[PDB]
Length: 370
Ligand SMILES: CCOC(=O)c1c(C)[nH]c(C(=O)N(CC)Cc2ccc3c(c2)OCO3)c1C
Image (cartoon, rainbow, N blue to C red):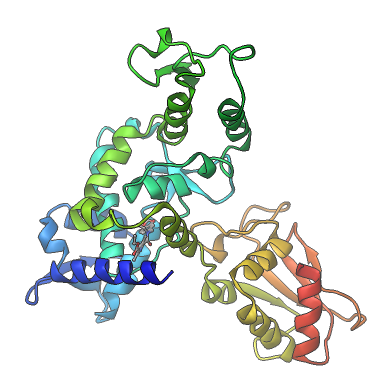
């Protein structure tokens, strides 16, 4: 709380001291080749050059304020799975993770080092990017261990079984060793040296669960993660992150998930209504009134998910029909004003009856959502 506020000020003050008063960090890339061009221009600089005031300009545009736009666009474009560095999770929708098969590109480690530098530059200049990584990824990047509690949301079944180990006498029921498996070929991993020959007992099961928790996230991505963290720490040294505790890191990480209302409203299709009509202004008014958890519940009420792809509301998918985005739709219909708004989750549509006032829309929409 108030100690977190002050820790953030110490961090920002320390970072500001590393920025030279004179000098600039010059970048000039195109929008359609921002990843490859930024890769070559950034990997040419010293870490101290990256700490200079950003001097950015796009391909052939006049545009200071362009450096904010450049960094934000590069932060989202570098996570695009086309580049083979990151892939979507099969545990939670629209979440990202390092692709363990990134070894295909033999220069992958220099690209992960580059991604780390850009993530470090975002923190350095005060940008909050909703990268969509898991809480364990972000804790590890910020220099802290993963907690068993952080596994519950990613892998509830593994979490339940590791919790079972810690809370019960395993002796008459389980016969595990410090060796774990995962995939086409089956790969064995010894959690600690000679692990295959170390049976899990009451005496060492705490170490077993602790090692298994880390492996569940680090599995096949350890070299990639190390290079990423290396780039990140060239901008954000690990000692400056030491004061933040597990709880403060969870608050900072949860704040990254903020739904972008600008991107939501810019990418909303309107059916039988205009952008200035009372029903549409009242809907966006009620959304602004809702806290984050209520904004997430509204997004889940209409789309079935509490998140949107990394590209944003423009990449929103529908369930059926021709391939292509199915934008979030506000549909003003002809219906009973006592009726609730109706969600058509297959098509990301909310059918809204013609309410008389803002206060009636707010209550009906809140009743539908809660
Ligand atoms: C401990 C103090 O934390 C901070 O002050 C802080 C600030 C100012 N920004 C960030 C932050 O946004 N990220 C963490 C690196 C997420 C992120 C950035 C760039 C990305 C990305 C995700 O996906 C690819 O590009 C944090 C945590």
